[PDB]
Image 1: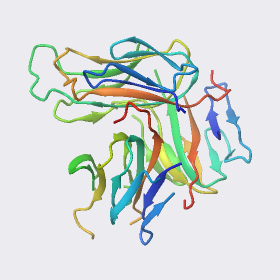
Image 2: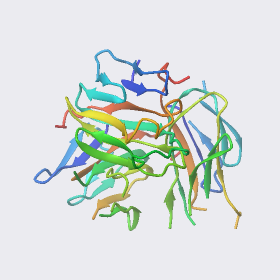
Image 3: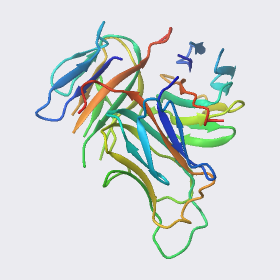
Length: 96
Length: 100
Length: 123
């Protein structure tokens, strides 16, 4: 099941069975999508900006402290977080 | 794994026994009890389950959450006015026998 | 077969379990569960507030992970989803806690949990 997490400091990018990889790290807190699909971004900023490509998809400040949600992402798509977050591929139907 | 998506225009109902059955634009019926994840995006108003409002949107926002749904339920995304990087979809996550 | 999951309520249902072999969760008490298995879990649910509640204690409904509040609900006028996706470890508990027991309608309130993955990375 394709997953990744970055990471809690001093953890960096970690990765679970990427074969073929669905995801590829870019810098810190940032990866790139290699494979179209429905993904679940999760993460935490406790006991901040989530970005898909150039614009913001979540802005944690606020009744819960969980980052992310479910999103269709496509090849070359980036996610950046501007304490961890990770991603899991749920499905790749037809059609995305 | 059973899922369906509507839009973005001019795409319609895209579908992947079925767990869901389209009704018309933006609207589907649930054919299977289960735990479902509804997702999507509204690029600028409300999500319904059997005529009751479950989310209301007012920037591009996220549609959905996780919902147990039963045979017969419908899911609709309604706009005040027509006047579209807008889509929504559903994936079936599980069907434990305790969802009925 | 699977995913491993559990649900509490709505009343009269208590803890119900599916795909418990081998178990990922242990019931601890009403509305409260223990994690048996490290994992990526998705927590979901419905809180139905008593919109006519008006006793002494202030209104608030909370989801906890151990001693940390992870979701707080103070609007008594609408039925609200609870949960999220979390990395969870053996001995973590998740509990859903009402400031007083008539702040919620328990015949329409529940929460459950599903195991999405164990990456062989968390802890």
